[PDB]
Each structure stands twice: as structure tokens, then as C-alpha cells.
Amino acid sequence: MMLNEVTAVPGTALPVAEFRDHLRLGTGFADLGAEDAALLSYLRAAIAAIEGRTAKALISRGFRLALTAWRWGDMQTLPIAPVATVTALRLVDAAGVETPVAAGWRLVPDMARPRIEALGAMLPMIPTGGRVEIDFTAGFGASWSALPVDLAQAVFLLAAQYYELRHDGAAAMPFGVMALIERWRTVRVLGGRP
Amino acid sequence: MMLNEVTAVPGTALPVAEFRDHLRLGTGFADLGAEDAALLSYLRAAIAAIEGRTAKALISRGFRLALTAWRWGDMQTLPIAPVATVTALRLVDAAGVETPVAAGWRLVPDMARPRIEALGAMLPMIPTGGRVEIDFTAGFGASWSALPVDLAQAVFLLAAQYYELRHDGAAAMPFGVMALIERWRTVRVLGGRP
Amino acid sequence: MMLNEVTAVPGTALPVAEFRDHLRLGTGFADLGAEDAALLSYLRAAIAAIEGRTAKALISRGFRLALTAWRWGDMQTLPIAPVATVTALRLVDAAGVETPVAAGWRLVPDMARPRIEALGAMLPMIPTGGRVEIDFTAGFGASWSALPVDLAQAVFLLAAQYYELRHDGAAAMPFGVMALIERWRTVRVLGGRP
Amino acid sequence: VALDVHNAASAWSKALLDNAARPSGAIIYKGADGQGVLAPEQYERLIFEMETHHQGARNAGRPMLLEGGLDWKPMGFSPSDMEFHETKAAAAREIALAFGVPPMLIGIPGDATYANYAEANRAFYRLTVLPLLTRVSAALAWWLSGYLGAQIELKPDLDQVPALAVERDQLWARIGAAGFLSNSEKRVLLGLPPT
Amino acid sequence: SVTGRIVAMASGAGRPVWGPRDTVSLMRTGFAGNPVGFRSVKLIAEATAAVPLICPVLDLLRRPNAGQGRAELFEALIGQILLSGNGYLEAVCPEPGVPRELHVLRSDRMAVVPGADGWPVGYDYTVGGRKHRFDMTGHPDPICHIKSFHPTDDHYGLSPMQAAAVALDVHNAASAWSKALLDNAARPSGAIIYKGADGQGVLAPEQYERLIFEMETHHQGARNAGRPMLLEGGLDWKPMGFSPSDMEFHETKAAAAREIALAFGVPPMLIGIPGDATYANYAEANRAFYRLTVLPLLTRVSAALAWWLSGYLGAQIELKPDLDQVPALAVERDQLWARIGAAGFLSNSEKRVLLGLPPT
Amino acid sequence: SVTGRIVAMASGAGRPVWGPRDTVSLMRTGFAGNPVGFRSVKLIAEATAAVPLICPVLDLLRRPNAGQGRAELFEALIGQILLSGNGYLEAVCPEPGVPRELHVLRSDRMAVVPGADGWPVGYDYTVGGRKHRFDMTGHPDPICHIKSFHPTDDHYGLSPMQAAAVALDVHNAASAWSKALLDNAARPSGAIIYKGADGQGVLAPEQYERLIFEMETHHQGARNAGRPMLLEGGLDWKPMGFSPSDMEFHETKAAAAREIALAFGVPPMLIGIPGDATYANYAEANRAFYRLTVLPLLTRVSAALAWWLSGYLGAQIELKPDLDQVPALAVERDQLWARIGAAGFLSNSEKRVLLGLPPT
């Protein structure tokens, strides 16, 4: 289970022109672009902070889930939660040959449990000494407008903070950064074997 | 259970002209200068914070509840609470034949526990692999004026807070944001198997 | 188990030109005056503080893991976590004949527990006195842009702190340095014999 | 109901012995901060001084120096024995109650109701065996006589069944000691062919 | 027999029916694994072999085959019935009548065939991939199949170990709980905590070898039990305990060790498990053992040998346990001889016919 | 027989089959390691040697070889059966009938060969790397192979120590728990804490030898038990305790010490382990010992000596335990002589034939 990203976010999909409206920089100056190189450096640093505390994705970039042994006999819950249209469960071999498999696997969409449950009571078997990478595109939407807005606000509450204080300097809201995140975190109570 | 919204708000349904009056009317600097479309972006962030803490809907948007297995035998509590009129309970199969049903169920509306509660003991079974899918319209009313005004004030107490201070800065009111929400939260005491 | 690095960073791979922008860009005195090669000496001190607390590598440097006895029968978890492609598992004897092996093991990559996990139950045994030695390349990517951006921000929140104040002077942020690190630390609960 | 109590209380203790993490302690390592991991160099030092010098029967009670930051919190296991021990043993008696066997014959634990197995085996062949057997044999005496012409009776022997010997000692020594009535007058009482 | 044809088709005629898969694993985990399941079968199988029999045919039973005596045969035969609910006896007949070889075929590797009319036509001894297909479509029918009572299955027995299969896994794992607790446990008898001036501080390897040598020599061991142990500034000794000391699942093991003994039918007094005194003084518990779980088992197997072996002979033979000169039934023999011996009214030959003597 | 021919070719004909791996390690850890496993075998193996036998051939058994007597032979023979489930007896035959040598071959270094038809053709005595290959392709068959009952294996015994192998490792490690707790433990009887003006402060070696000498002389020992111990500023005495004092795995060892005695079948009263009173007064528990685990064991080995040694003779001989003048069965002999001796109705010669007397 490695879970790397195939492609990153384009950067042009991030709302730098709206984050600048948030931070109260300035309206009609002739410069207007001295911060563009750094404002998206804090938006990518605040999304990636909330992508890890919530285990959500938010831009629907493509992922690659390269794993070897199945976690449970048939289920295989995916880590990145809001998914749609798993592309390919290409089953690599011990070395080399990569054979994509329709394989009779389904996809159960959920924000909490994005399973990949199999229908033939057993997922496609795994060549001993070989991995099973799964290409899937997981996230809310393609553009910034398709997000839940409270999670989009939690980026703006957080990336404004990184813009206003640079080093770790200490400085209570009703719905702060944390209270907006908490309905998107994963609530789990299993430490067991299954 | 994905539960994505079919359509969002139009934006013209939101009380941006009224929220400018809750921001500075009768006392203030003047009407002053506020990026109008910015003020729409804080109302959508305060509603989506109260739509999540209360599990209400507040604008009567259209929903699509596509879940695989029925939880109870017949009950199926709907999460987004103030509901009216299931659009359709179409039932897709594993291939996508999408055969709707038109009888066998009677939505029992309620602000506490909206249900589906089919007739007798038979609720439409699920094609194996073929997720069931329920389209409904949930919320109070089409315009902003049809809301309970205490819940509308919790938006204005919250959307003004996101306007007055940007980052997560520190700052116990009797009926604050939190005290106006708690009579609209869902009070549940089940952690059990049914 | 010495685990010395083969090569360090080049120094030109580090974002000194970007860290000057995280130090004072968009707000500040001017670009101001900063001893450039000093700013490289605080990034190497903040990465090496986060390479130690997270047991990650972040630049994809080359390592050499020379240990005497295998801990398990076959497993051999690698400490530096994000790995890719064992360079060689050469096996030196007590005199230094250095006979490499080229098969019998299949590195199973993972950000949690990278392994060696030989085929079957036979992992290459050790010549008596002749330490085994594993060369691998561990880290995210060759350039600074291939990193998770939340972990990159923990460097910039920390390397700026070593720049802003020199001695150990006193000074609770929501996603501070410590809150961005904790989803990359290694969570272990074994104090046992295996 | 008493089967499902006894089945699940017995499966309670099975899966408790199979799903349970008790530790015999926990070496808490906070650090200078409130949180801090220890490096995998330090961690293999910490295993090897725990694997070799502290675990096992042969290392039971080493004095265990704890420097700054380290601390050992010993855990316990507060319900140790007796997980639904009496509710299983009460349900193990209600199953034996329903079929009518005494608790002494089957071997379940419990308070001494019957004394010395001359009773409990005699109670077993009088309250739940011989009433059961004389009811089935009364149906074989009537169903099989429908195949014959003449009707046949078919009853349990209630003689030379060795659990009823205490009802046979008690009846032979009563009439054998009754010396007033003569010899042939008591062979007809005990069931003997008269002479 | 008229309904025999209907159940045969559902299972599938001419094809082997296996029944329980996990039968071989209950043997290794429940009979070679724990002593209670081990002793309970060995206590019964060595008791049924010791009981004499009443009929020629017993000349076969006395010497069945090479290296497998009379008493050794029934231990193998009953030892399969208690373990897997099924007993098998192959007869090899070089001669036409009373075949001079008997072999207990183990019931792990034996499978039934339902056949046409529901009663079996084939038995399959399956070792490796190799089958044999014994045939029951004849008159001598070369294997006697002794079933324990099974209400739900139509072809096999129930094997009391299967009914106690939860209580075996409690007793196997509670006993392995205390084993691995004695092998994975770090108790210290204390901890010399060294904080320092800071909240954290190590002590130098000069100071650390000083701390071992005053602990190795002067404080550990039986002979240094209770030295007054000066603690300077920074040092502190926190003595640890071990709060559950005895009794790790002690009663749930002792309760599961009785439910295993319950299923095979041995009394708790015979096997040696601790427990409340149910039976009194071994004149009862040994007499209860040979009356509730040995002699009913032996009169059921001997009734199958009385019918299978009579199919090789011409005349049918009865074959029952002796229920006489079996020395566990002496309290039922005192009680019956002193009853009729004290009955002085009926004459001498009138009680020799009651006690079973040849009259004179 | 027919099934056996198929079984051979699965495992491999002509090649040695070893069976148990750990049987060389259960002896050192279960028979030389703990007293309960030691005494349990010694209690049985010294009981089977004491039982007389009923038949010439017994002249061999009385004096088998030099330095290995009659009673010493069965202690070696049963001592291998209880330890590793297998008994072996090599016979050296210079003469054709009744071979004048018997040797208990230890079952660690012996291995079977399945041969062609499944019944064994070879036994291999392997010490070091050196073999012997005894041959079974003849009539006298120079090794009797006494098997304990094993349901899963076709060539060996089950060895009750294997069934108690968890309870041995509990009893070995709980007993070694208390040994190393008495050997690795630092309890102090107190601690004189000296903080100082600072939070930390040592005391000078001038002051420290003053502190030892007032503690060595005036406070430690029986003769200084309870001195009032003035503590000035900075000094303080914190008395430590020892919270689990007795009873370190005391009942789990005593429950495991009973399960070892349970598996071999000895009663808890004979061996001397503590426990609840199951048997009453040793007229039963010694009679139970010679009826549930000695005489069934002895009548099974003697039935194999009656058949293996008769292969050297022409006529077959029976060889059974005496079951008479063995003084643990006197309570079964009182009970049977007083029953028939009090039966006055049947005459004098009619009861000498019942009790086993030569009639007159």
C-alpha cells in the first residue's frame, strides 16, 4: 500500500484570485501580482494539511494505489475517501507483465467507506511476489466550485494563517479551522484483526 | 451512500442584500465597501457549517441518495432532515437498466427522523450489485424567508464572523451561534446494531 | 547497523530561492539582506530535525544499511520509510569477498513498513562475521517539488524559526510544526521480542 | 433461551482468549516535548535490552533503570477469571433441567441435591426415562398390533434394570421380613412363579 | 427403505460424500493438544477394550491381524468413534467364511457413497490422491460402519469432540494464555528513575557502570533482600508490582476442563480434574462410568459386530458385553447377591436360577 | 491391508519416516526438567515392573541380558512408551527359538520404514549419522514395536507428554519464574532520600561514610530493629514495600502440576501434588492407579510380548498380568471373597470354583 499520486493539481484550478480577495491585499494597484508565486504555495500547503487530517482529496486528481496483499479477503477499503470511477486494477506479475483485469470487481461509493468489494466472493488473486496497483481518480470535483464550501473555508482559514505568520509563533472560534474539519475526518473504532 | 447534491444553490436565493444589512445597517461606517461576491462566499461557508452540524438543508436543494444495501428491513432514515416529496426511487441494476418504482413506499416526513418506511414489511429489494438510488428534495423553503428565523440568525452570526476576522484568531454569548444550533441538531443515542 | 548516507544532498536541490520567499515575500522589509549560504544551513537543520522525528528522507538520497544479523526470519523492516528500488544487497564476508546477491528477495514498498520480505521463508543468511549490507535509495523525489506539500511546509515553518531567533529563546498554532509532522511519524506499539 | 446463553457465554470466553491485547506493561516515552518518537537506532537498542534482559520467566524482576523521559507503567487485567461464569453455569443447569436429567448424572457443577447416585440414577429412570419409554412402547404396542390380528401389549420391564435396585431392595426386605404371612403368600407379591 | 430412493438423488448417487472438513484438525487441537480431551478418550477406549464378550467368532477378535491385538483393536476402533463419530472395519477374506483379518480404517480418509436406494454402495479410502472404492453391492458387505447418533446427517456420526469444540478451544487457549504470559512478560521489581536537573537527563557510561555494580552486587538477589538504598538528589526508586499474580483464566479453564469431560461422559472424579464432589467414593463414579458412557457404547459396537460378522457365518451370532466379572460393577453385584441370598424363604435352586448359576 | 498398500506409495516406500521432531526435547524439558513429569513416569514404570505375569519364555524375561534385570527391563520399556509413545525390543537369536537377549532400544534414534504393502519392512536405528536397518521381511521379526494409540499417525504412538506439552511449559516456567524472581530482585527495606537545599544535591564522601556507619551499626539487622532514627533537614526515609509477596503464579503452576498428572493418568493423591480431595483413603487411589493407567497399560504390552515371542516358539503362548496378589487390588478381593463366602446357599466346592481355587 503506497498510494502515490499520478498527477498533481494543475495549480490553475486553485482559487488564487479568490484567496487574494480573502486576505485583504489590495484592490486596484498596478502591481497586483507580486504574491501569486507565494499565495498558491500556501494554498497547496493548507490543502495538503487538510487532506491528511480528513483523509479527503478535494481536487479529484488521479491516484495510484500500489499494493501487494489484500487487507481483507474481499473488501479492500481505499484510503482517499471521496472516489468515483476506479479506472484500472491492472494486476502486475512477479516481474514485468501488467495485465489489466475487469476481474468482476465492483465499486461501492461512500465518503466514509470507499470500498472496492468483489462480486465473485474473492478479488482477483495476486501473483506471489507481485503487486496490484489500482488507478482511481478520487476527490469532490474538478474545479474549486464543486467542493463543500465549509471545507473550502477551512482551507481559507488555514492558508490565511500561514500567510500571516511565517514561523511557529503562538497566537477559540466557534467554527474554526478544526471545527469545520471534524465532520470530514474518518471516525474509526477498530484496532482489531478484522 | 454517496449523497451528492444534484444542484447547488443558485446564489441569487441567498440574502446577500440582507446580509449587507446585518453586517452594517443602522450603525456603522456607512454602507462602506464590501466585495459583494465575497459576501456570498461567506454565507455559503456559514450555511455549510450549519448544514453539517445540524444535518439540515436550509435552501431546499435537490439531493440524490444512492446507497447499496438497506440498513433496516423497512425503515431507511434519511440523513438530511427537513424533507418533502421523494422525486423518484429509481432502482439501477449492476449494468444500469434503471427501472424506477412508483409504489410500495410512503415517505413519512418529520424534522426528527425522516423515513421511507415501506408498506407492510416489503421494501424494494436491491439488485445484486445494482445500487438503489433515491432522489429527494430536502429543506425548509425555496426562498430565504421561509426559514426558521433563529436558524437564519445563526448563519448571520457566523457569516459575519468569517467576514470580521480572516485567520483563526482568538476573541460566550447567551444565544450565540452554538446555542441557536442545538435545537436543530440531531439527538441520537444509538451506537448499536439497529 | 550503521546506516550512513552514501551521498548527502547536493545543496542545489534545496529550495533556497523559495525559502527566501517563505521568509519575506509579499510582506516584509524588502527582499532585505540574508546570508544566502546561511539560509541553506537552516534548511539542512530543519530537514534533519524532521527526518529524525518522522523517519522519512524527503530528498531521495542514497543510503547504505549494513547490519550483522537479520532480526526476523525473513521480514527486515527498513527504517527510513519512503523507499524505492534496492540498489544492491551485496553480502560481504569476514574477510571482504563482497559477493552480491541478485534474487531471493523482493522489496515490498510502503510508507508505513518498508520491508525486504524474501521469497518463501529463506532470506540470504549471513557469513559468520561477514556483515550483510543493503544499499537503497529512500525518499519521495529528486527535486523539492515532488514532496507532500504539508511536510514541506513543516520544513519552512521550522527553518524560518531557526532563522528568526538564534538562541533557545521562549515565545500553540493549530497546524504548527508538530501538527504537520504527526501524520508522518511512525506509529509503533511493539516493545516485544518480535 | 438457555441454549443461546450457554452457547454465547462459552463463546464469550473463547473469543476473549483470542481477541484480547493485554500487555504486561508499557514503556512510555514522552520526550522533551509532549510527544516525541525515538529513532530506529534507539528503538532496536530498546528492543534488545527488553527482549534479552527483561522478558521471560528467566528475567522476572530486573531492576530496570529508567533515565529521563522513559517511564514504565505496568498494566493490569482487572476481570481476570470468571467471564459469565455463573450465568453459564446457571444456564448449563437449565438445559439439564428441561430434558429432566439430574445435574449429578451429567456432571455439571452445582449444589448437592441428590445424595449418592443410588437416588439420582433412580430418579433418572423414574422421572424422565421410564415415563418416556412407557409412552413410546405404548405406541409400538398399538401400531404394530394393527399389522397383527391379536393386539399385543408392550411395556418396559421395570425389573432387572439396575438403577431400580434401591426400589427392589426396599420391597424384598419389607415382605421377606414380614414373617406372619406364609411362604407362598409372598412369592405372589414379589412376582415370583409360585410353588 | 421406500423413502431411501428420494434422499439418495439429492446428495448424488455414485459420488463421494465427505461431511465434515475440519475433522482432522480437531484431532490435533483437541486430542493431541490438551490433556483433558486426551485423557477422556484414552480412559474410555482402554475401558471398552478391557470388557470381555459373550458369543469361533471371538477367535478372530482375539487375534485380528499382525501387530494389532484384541485390546489394541478396540482402542483403535472406539478411538475413531469418539474422535470422528465413525468406526470402520475392513475384513480380508482369503477363505470364504469368517475372514481372518480385521483392520480399523481411520475415518479421516474414509468417505461414503449414497448409491441408488440411499443405503451405501461405496466407501472410499482416500490417501493422497489415491482412492480404493470398496463395494457394498454384495452380500458380505466388507466394512461395518458404526455410526454414533447424528440427527441431522444421514451418513455419519456426531463425534462428541465436535459438541465440545468450543470448550476445547477455551481450554487450549487458556492454557496457552498462561504459557505465553510466562514467556512474554516484563515485570520489574522496581525502577531506578533518574530525572536530573532538567526534566530529562541521561547518566554517563561512567556513572552507569557504577550504577550496575552497586545494583549487581549489593541490591539484587536473595542475599541482598532489603538493603537501605541511599537515594541522592535526582534518583528515586519506584517499586513496580504485578497486579494479577495468580489465576489467569483459572476458573474458566477449570470450567472448560469439566465441559470437555462432560461431553465424552467421563465423570470429573475419574479423569482427575478438580471440582465439587458430585460422586462420593469411587465405588459410584467408576460404576457410573461403566454404565452411562462405556457399556452403552460397548453394547452398541458389539451389536454391530454381532451382525456384520454373522454375515460371513451361516448362523447368526449374538455378541454382548459380559456384565459379569467386570470389577467396576461389584457394587451392583454385592447388592443383587445379598438381596437374593438373604431371601431365605425361597429355596436353594430357586435363587441359583436368579443369580445366574447352573442349578444342582 | 488393501488400504495399506495405497498408503505406502503416498509417503514413499523404502525411505525412513521420522514422525515427531521434538520428542528429544520433551525428554529434557519434561522428564529431566520438572518433578511432576518426572515422578509421573517413575510412578507408572515402577508399577508395571512390579506386576507378576502368567505364562520357559519367562526365564528370558527374568534375565534378559547383563546388567539389565527383569524389573529394569520394563522400567526401560514403559519408560519409552510414556515418553515417546513407542517401545522397542531387539532380540539376538544365536539359537532359533526363544532368543536369549532383549534390549530396550530408545525411541529417539529409531525410525520406521513403510515398505511396499504399508506394514513396515525396516526399522532404522540412527545414532550420529550411522544406521543399522533392521529387517522385517522375515517371520521372527526381530523387533516388537509397541505403539500407543495414535489416531492421525499410521506408524507411531501419541506419547502423553506430547498431550501435556503445554502444561509442562507452564509448570517449567512458573517454577523458573519464582527462581529468577528470588535471584533477580532488588527490594530495599527503605530509602534514605537526600534532596538538599537544591532539588538535587549529593552528600560528600566524608558525610557518606558517616551515613553508612550510623546505618551499618545502629539501624540494620535484627538487633537494631526499630531505632527511632532522627532525620535532620534535607534527609528523609521512605520505606518501600513489596506488594506481591507470596504466590507468584502459585495456582497456575498448581493447576498445571495437576494437568501433567492428569495426562499420564496418575491420581493427584499418589504423586503428592496438592488439590481437592477426590479419592478418599488410598485404598481407592492406589486401586484406581492399578486399574485405569497401569494394568490396561501392562496388559497391552504383555499382549505384544505374547505374540512377538511366540513367533520364535512353535506353539503360541499367552502372557497376561496376574491380577492376583498385587496388593493394590486387595479391596477388589475382599469385596469378592466376602460376597461369595457369605453366600451360604451354594456349597463348598461350588465357591472354590468361583474364587479361583483348585477344587477339592
Image: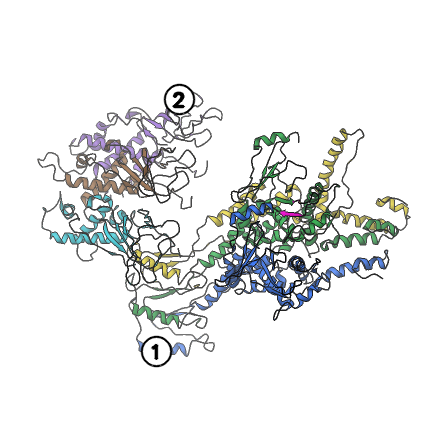
Chain colours: A brown, B purple, C cyan, D yellow, E green, F blue
Give x and y (percent) for residue A10: 21, 36
Instruction: Tell me the element at label 1.
Output: helix
Region rendered in magenta: E92-103
Q: Where does the C terminus of chain C fall, quadrant-wise?
A: bottom left
Q: Is residue E100 on the magenta stretch?
A: yes
Residue D187 visible in the snapshot: yes
Image side of residue B183 versus residue F351, left or right:
left
Residue at numbered disc 2:
B99
Give amino acid for label 1: Glu
Residues F130 and C39: in front is F130
Q: Residues within 10 Å of mark 2 (few under 14, many from 20)?
A: few
Give x and y (percent) for residue E277: 65, 55
Residue E44 visible in the snapshot: no
**Extreme residue toward the left, this view:** A30
Give amino acid for label 2: Thr
Residue at numbered disc 1:
F209
Q: Badge 2 sits on which subunit? A: B
Q: Is residue D108 on the magenta stretch?
A: no
| Same chain? Circles 1 and 2 | no
Q: How crowded is mark 1: few (under 14 residues within 10 Å), some or many (20 or more)?
A: few
Image side of residue A26 versus residue E293, left or right:
left
Q: Badge 1 sits on which subunit? A: F
Answer with the quarter of the image where residue B92 lies: top left
- Note whether B131 is above or below C21 in the view shown: above
